[PDB]
Image (cartoon, rainbow, N blue to C red):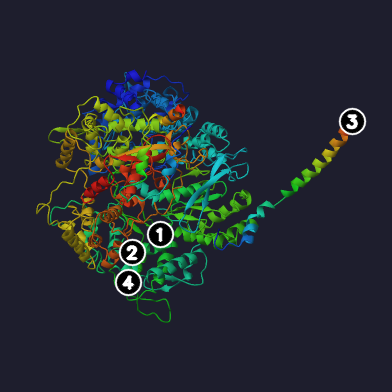
Amino acid sequence: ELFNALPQPLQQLSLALAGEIPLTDHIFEQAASTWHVQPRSLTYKLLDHIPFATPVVVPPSIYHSLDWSKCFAVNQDRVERIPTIDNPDDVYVPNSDIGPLLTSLHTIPDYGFLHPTIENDATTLRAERARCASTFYKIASSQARQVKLDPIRMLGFLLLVQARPRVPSGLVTDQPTRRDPTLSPALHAIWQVMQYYKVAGVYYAPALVVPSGAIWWIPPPGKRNVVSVQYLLTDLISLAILAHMTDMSPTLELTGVLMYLRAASSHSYAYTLLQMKSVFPALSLRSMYRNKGFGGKAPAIEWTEPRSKYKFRWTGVTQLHDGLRPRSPSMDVPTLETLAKYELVDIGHTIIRERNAHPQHNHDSVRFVRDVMALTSGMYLVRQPTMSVLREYSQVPDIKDPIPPSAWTGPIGNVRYLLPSVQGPARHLYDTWRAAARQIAQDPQWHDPLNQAIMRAQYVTARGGSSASLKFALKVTGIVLPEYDDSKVKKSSKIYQAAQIARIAFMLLIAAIHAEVTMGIRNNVIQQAISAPHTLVANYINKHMVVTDKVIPLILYASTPPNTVVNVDIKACDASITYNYFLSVICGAMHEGFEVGNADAAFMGVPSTIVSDRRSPVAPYSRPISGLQTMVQHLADLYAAGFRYSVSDAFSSGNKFSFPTSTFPSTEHTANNSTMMEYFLNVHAPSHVKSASLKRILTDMTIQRNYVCQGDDGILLLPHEAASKISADDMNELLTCLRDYGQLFGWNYDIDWSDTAEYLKLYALMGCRIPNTSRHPPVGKEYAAPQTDEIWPSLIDIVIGHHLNGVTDVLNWREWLRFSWAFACYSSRGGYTNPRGQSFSAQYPWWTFVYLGIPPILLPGQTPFIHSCYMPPGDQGMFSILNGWRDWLISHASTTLPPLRHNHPVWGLSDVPSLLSQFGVYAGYHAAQHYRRPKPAPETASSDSINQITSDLTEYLFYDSALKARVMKGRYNWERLSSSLSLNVGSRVPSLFDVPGKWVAAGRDAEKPPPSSVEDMFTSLNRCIRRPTHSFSRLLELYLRVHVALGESIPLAIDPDVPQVAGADPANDDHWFKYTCLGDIPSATRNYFGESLFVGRVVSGLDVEAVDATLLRLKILGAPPEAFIAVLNGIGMSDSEAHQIAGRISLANAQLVQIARVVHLSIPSSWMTLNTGPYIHHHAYDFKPGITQPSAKSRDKSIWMSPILKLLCTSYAMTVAGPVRTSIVTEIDGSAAALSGNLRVWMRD
Amino acid sequence: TETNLIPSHHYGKAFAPLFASNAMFTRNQRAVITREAFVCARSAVAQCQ
Amino acid sequence: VLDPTVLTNAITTISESTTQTISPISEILRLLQPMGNDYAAFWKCIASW
């Protein structure tokens, strides 16, 4: 059997994780070091223990391999472009073996790496062959790197979860699992593949994974190590996991496997999958319910006031019928024919046979749609960077109606105006952009110095950026010499550094007109600042424009079978904006709108030059243009020469380039979406659609209503003459007049109408959101780099991003929670070996994952699986566990450990901090608060870290216009106030002196932190484990006074048999409860949620919720009005603008969540997709005057006190794993005015 | 409701695809047969007594 | 069946200010509600008559 085949430590853990033994730190530690010590290939032996009955037979043609030498030609001078076999797009990877080009690594024999000799040739002398070999090894060991860890390890956790059956929890609606590991086609095809890699009884994995990349095993003579098998195992593992967290039927699962075995067998594994990526949502999600007899329940959502403030409201239940079926035809004819060419038709007829057995909209039907959509291979697809640029970036759009050259005026310097005669879609684009440019040019908003410092903060990216080259190898065109390091400089050309390099003349200088030399360097801060009036106008078109309340509510309303919905996705909206049509009308219109401004007004540091103006043939005359028009003359000299790309990929060896194209990797190809559809519904489609009925429908349709634009995506929802839509006459003739409308100016519209709704990759069928589990797979994670970046505790943040991202999805939790726990444990045994010294290690105890968000399986006093996966992370969850069993550990430590002599007011004389320290709670509490990334070493050239000149002069870019005085008035008037009078913080309130330090902390975050720093991380980590402070935190020790007891479940928010979310059916215990007790559509009252944050305009270096808390955190205390203006001057706001905020910030009319933010009680990301708005302020009492005690009566202080107490209640109410229920503060240990005073001691810090 | 809602326009927009064909005139054809078959059941029963 | 969630539910919904020190709802709720023998004294009195 599988269970008695495992190692002693693992058998105990599998038992422990399953629920039989609450796991202790000894169970956790021995199971952690059992993984890292034993060889990784040994967990493939466990496949040989389970018997198998699935009829999946792998072909012997998997291991055949067309060699890489035919499929990796250096067509250009140093470009390893793969010569496609049969296509332009067959370039993902070749299904070759790396048999010859491997030399055995001496540490792990029979596991080789790139040949030492071959690598040298590529670096020194190109070997059309000696570099084509190197670009094949660094792709196949990078395509086998798109994975969270070793996938052989991720399979090893699934055998732990399937080692034992789960202990029955005791809940009524707890279904034991139906999945049998002896009946699974995924991990039977793994073992059938793994027979080929067998040298005398032992298994060799074909590619052990190292943070530099994969290490491929060297086959003995006669066998081939084909690179596709490692990806064929990475998908088959990811199917073996997604069919044990989904309860996928064995027959349905079998079809998915045959999809993979055909793909490994053909020439390219990666390529085959891509051509059949949409072959599985089309069979099921797109085509559900077309048979007669359709009819279940579906929600009845309303659009309240449609024009703006999309505020959908869940109002009722519809009863479906044979009418309002999906009018669109099924995808069986089209996808199956496409499917037919790869010889899997039989896997198409199986899924069609299953789908015809779900005729009506049930829980079982919409669970089936998630089962088929979890069959698409969610692995990422690495392609050579040089090769990728050729096939993606450079595709010039085809225009079926160009602007004639006699439709422009004469030139005015560089740009041209459009003539008034030429109507069409070009005229509406010109008129909607010129009218918006003549609103921006007459505006007081962008002349304020704080708005300038915000705009300079958007250019140096606080998040993102790319590998820009430099500036002074591009300023040899100019005369301006750039700044150099005063002291040793660490940051290399960081977007921030570019600002640092030239900050002498407001981050730009009309002496710096050499911004057009080498742009967009990616595999510029002065081109982002030349493009100021291009995204200033695009942020006026995008006035009407989050996912949780502006998309999730929508997708649902659009999917209901009243209104039929066309979803419009534009393919390559980047590569459709060209200067031949789109970007010349834009720069033409902005230069026309920018004349209603004062024609001598400089903008953003660019003066007001003159221009030729030759647009009249009888009188050309020099004309002074404005400052904003001067940027347009340099935008038109930049957009017309395209964008340079200095792509130099590290995958291919010598591949360096200089690439010009017309694609930008900001919000304009978002902004052009609405105005080009506004012309469709009003002018173009009523002009010709050849249908009397069709024309009638369009006339009553606008674009503010009936269209929701975002990015390149968008949903077009028709007027209410809806379900009654003739698909032959109306909805297909509306589509061909749409798809030919976009082709007359290059926009390749890709319409795919069906009665689901796709909106930025969140599908929903019939009022029920369907999560795509292959969008973020369990084993898969992109990296997009040769060498990765994994020190050691950067695996823990992956695990919490692996667990919580699977629970936004309605993945079954019990199979999932156990899997997450097993995976979490592996991520607790780490190490670091010095290059010239001793090796090191660390051991995170469990309870360091309970503090991070993973709920525990079995505490020592309970029954397993009663802590829900919606438990909030941190102190809200550490309270909501300790509030659960405080009646247990007090009774247990009264009959074990001796009583303490003094009294802890939360407990009694029963001594539980010496019991909590025995269970390892404090060692888990102080471990996760300890930092995880290695600190950049504190090394400078001079002044003991002071007088740094790259940090002190990034402030010069942020201090233009005597704003510098306001942040100096802020840090003076606050330090005069706080450190001597009262409210003495000791640390800085979030002022503007932190963010030039924050650009360096996000800039000096260099790779390879030296061995001096990561050893210092390992030593500091080991001290906070061995001597974790016995005392808890200062917030948690005050939260534990509250005794929260919860009553019977609250009146429901959804008739709990309409299925709202992809399988949160009674197979799932709590996910069906928390999605029907609470509702979806998370729009609530304006006294709870309504997105205030009473500052709004942050400087982008500051957290918005750090200002919003500390503006409230003073108002809780006895703050003088001076302490509000001194903090708000620290952000840089003017004294007049700070005063209007200093009077506003009252607890009366303050969002309930904001008050909770003061003491760091946040609504977490786990239930952001839930309607916890009315739950907190209706139910979850802070005082129910008959159950509660009069001792816990927050009297006068209740305005700010109640929010905290209502969020401690709902933290306990979502942590337990049943229906949500009314949670009452029973009593507080010590009175509530003796706790409200206790928080105000902490709120002075 | 909508802001500028002209309701006789809104109903003519809405009630147009319900009078598109013989939806109403199937109940009339069903009613005549349920009258002839009712007398022919009343006649044929009361003639055999 | 003397169920004491009828007396309690009538007193608990009178509204009083929480800023007063002595609270005249919490006094009488302390007076009767701790319960001994589910109020069986009443039966003894009736039994005795």
| Marking on residue A532 | 2
Residue A833 pos. (x, y %): 17, 34
In this rendering, the answer to whether A15 lies above or below A1233 is above
Q: Is residue A480 above or below residue B16?
A: below
Q: Is residue A865 left or right of residue A829?
A: right
Q: Give, as a three-letter code, the residue at label 2.
A: Ala
Q: CA distance from mark 4 to mark 2?
A: 11 Å
Residue on which disc 3 sits: B48
Q: Which residue is mark 4?
A: A627
Q: Where does the image place residue A290, in percent across and percent down from the top left?
A: 59, 40
Q: Are marks 2 and 3 on the same chain?
A: no
Residue depth check, mark 3 versus mark 1: number of the one nearer the observer: 3
Element at badge 1?
helix
| Residue A946 image-quadrant placement | bottom left
Q: Nearer the viewer, residue A1029 or A1043?
A: A1043
Name the residue tied to disc 1: A668
The chain identifier of the residue carrying mark 1 reads: A
Q: State whether discs 4 and 2 lie on one chain.
A: yes
The subunit carrying tag 3 is B
**Residue A10 or residue A102, whichever sits in front:** A10
Q: Same chain for marks 1 and 2?
A: yes
Element at label 2: helix
Distance CA(mark 4)–CA(mark 3): 106 Å
> How many numbered marks does the figure carry?
4
- Label 3 sits on a secondary structure element that is loop
Q: Earlier in the sequence, mark 1 or mark 2?
A: 2
Give the chain letter at badge 2. A
Between circles 4 and 3, the one closer to the viewer is 3
